[PDB]
Image (cartoon, rainbow, N blue to C red):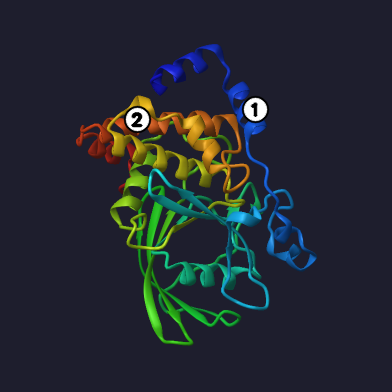
Amino acid sequence: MEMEKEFEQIDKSGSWAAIYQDIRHEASDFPSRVAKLPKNKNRNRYRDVSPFDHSRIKLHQEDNDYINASLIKMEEAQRSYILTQGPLPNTVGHFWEMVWEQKSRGVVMLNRVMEKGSLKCAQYWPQKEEKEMIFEDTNLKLTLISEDIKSYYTVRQLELENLTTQETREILHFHYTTWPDFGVPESPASFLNFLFKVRESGSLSPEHGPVVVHCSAGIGRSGTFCLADTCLLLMDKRKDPSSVDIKKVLLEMRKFRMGLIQTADQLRFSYLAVIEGAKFIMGDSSVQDQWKELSHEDL
């Protein structure tokens, strides 16, 4: 069944909430014992969002290897992602340690530091070239090199230095700044334009470690990003849009981290993004230029 027709069936019958509840019911449940250890209580932003033991990222340190981060491994698509929470004031150093150890080239941030009047993430990267950050617990230094600000998203070029070895790497920070406080964006053009900017950078490519994706809890907006990317990749590999079942891909991803896609309107939005993205995958290259125009990214 073409997903565009499934989409109309669900929309016309008003059954998004019902489909979404079925997904919750069917989703995997695996233990998350390490997350719940008392020594780790101050490393978790939300009590009800934990990585499963089997897919958690381990820090390469002997004292405490725990970070609230999961490795999503999509075997058929041949793409991996690290999904993580917005770093806390005491875990910013752990965050950058993970980036270094996993050899990531890109960090995708889908939230603002302050949303709905409350703090959702620590300010974990430098805002001025001349004021670099030093993370003393993990022996890393971070410098802003350059920033490219567009209307609803910003790309930053960062240099991460391992102070123990003096090795350095370029990290790209992709910051989507215009996800609304409530609901989802009305059109996915801006979303897709951003996703293909991340792709074009090489950050999702197999020669690098997995991209790090986060929002506040690392399951909702972050899940929507990974779900759309994997679905479009699978349609690419097969050049067959009707083979790909978004609901099945989502349940597969939910084997690796709980709760991905937090609302029925994020699910609907995921279908819309994949449907519109398909036009490009199946060979209408000009659509990419239309997304840029519609996104009103400039100025």
Query: Circle 2 is placed at which residue position?
Result: 276
In the rendered structure, the answer to whether residue 37 lies left or right of residue 225 reads right
**Nearer the N terminus, badge 2 or badge 1?**
1
Residue at mark 2 to residue at mark 1: CA–CA distance: 25 Å
Q: Residue at x 21, y 32 (%)?
A: 284
Query: Circle 1 is placed at which residue position?
Result: 21
Does the image show residue 126? no
Measured as percent of width and height from the top left, residue 160 is found at: 43, 75
Q: Name the secondary structure under disc 2.
A: helix
Give the number of the disc on residue 197: none
In the rendered structure, the answer to whether residue 51 lies left or right of residue 279 reads right
In the rendered structure, the answer to whether residue 87 lies left or right of residue 201 reads right
- Please count the marks in the image: 2
Rate crowding at label 2 as few (under 14), some (14 to 19) or many (20 or more) other CA atoms within 10 Å: some
Callout 1, which amino acid?
Gln
Rate crowding at label 1 as few (under 14), some (14 to 19) or many (20 or more) other CA atoms within 10 Å: some
Q: Residue at x 68, y 57 (%)?
A: 45
In the image, residue 283 above or below residue 292: above
Does the image show residue 148? yes
Could you tell me if the residues under marks 2 and 1 are in contact, i.e. CB atoms within 8 Å?
no
